[PDB]
Amino acid sequence: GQLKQRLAALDQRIAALKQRRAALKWQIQG
Amino acid sequence: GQLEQELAALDQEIAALEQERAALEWQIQG
C-alpha cells in the first residue's frame, strides 16, 4: 500500500495547489 | 508582474508533482 499512500498524498497536495492557483488567477484579474 | 511569476512557479510545481503521479500510476499497473 506504500504506492497507494504516495498517490493519495500527491492527490491531496495537488488539489490544494490547484485551489491556490484558482485564487491566484482571480487576483491576476483583479 | 510578480503575480504572473508566482502563477508560473505554481504550474511548474504542479507539473513536477503530476509527473510523480504519472510514474506512480504506471508502477501500480505492474
Image (cartoon, coloured by chain):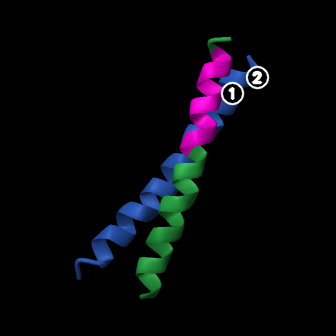
Graded by Cα atoms within 10 Å as few (under 14), some (14 to 19) or many (20 or more), the crowding at tag 1 reads: few
For label 2, the residue is B2
Q: Amino acid at mark 2?
A: Gln
Left or right: A8 with respect to A27? left
Q: Nearer the viewer, residue A16 or B21?
A: A16
| Residue type beneath disc 1 | Gln
Residue at 59% x, 50% y: name it.
A16
The residue nearer to you, when weighing B27 against A6, is A6
Which chain does the green colour mark?
A
Q: Quadrant of the C terminus of chain A?
A: top right
Residue A8's place in the image compared with B10, above or below, is: below
Q: CA distance from mark 2 to mark 1?
A: 5 Å
Q: Secondary structure at mark 2?
A: helix
Please give the residue where the numbered disc 1 appears in the rendered image: B5
Magenta extent: A18-28
Q: Are marks 2 and 1 on the same chain?
A: yes
x then y, percent, for residue B20: 46, 63
Contact between marks 2 and 1 (CB within 8 A): the answer is yes
Q: Residue at x 54, y 42 (%)?
A: A18
Q: Chain of mark 2?
A: B
Quadrant of the rendered image containing residue A26? top right
